Length: 68
Length: 61
Image 1 (cartoon, chains in turn brown, green):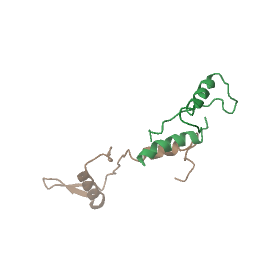
Image 2 (cartoon, one colour):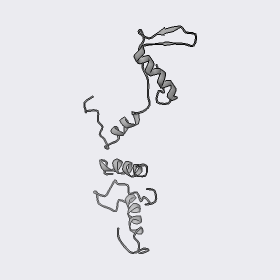
Image 3 (spheres, chains in turn cyan, orange):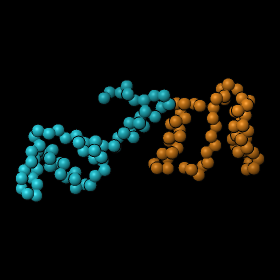
Image 4 (cartoon, helix red, strand yellow):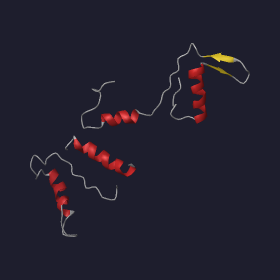
């Protein structure tokens, strides 16, 4: 789990892209770790304010009836 | 409210707010809160105006 992914150094994002495609990493000692048996989930705070803006778009209405 | 400066352009709405507690207006104007917002408050600048309009559009109170 990668919480607060929206607030992170840009260089960390470069590592993440490598993991998603290559599927493995190598540390400073040269040993290679595996990621073919893991699930990556990242939690971002962005878009939540957009969702609540849809909830407060009208006085007493929301957008939950729209298609997912 | 349109009028000459100092003739009571802002004082006209002043008495309406006080009469709200005494229910001196009709039922259509009853249960309504009147807010006198200064023009100096307001993309970034229009966000406050849009939020105020949105919260008072579908409400009507």
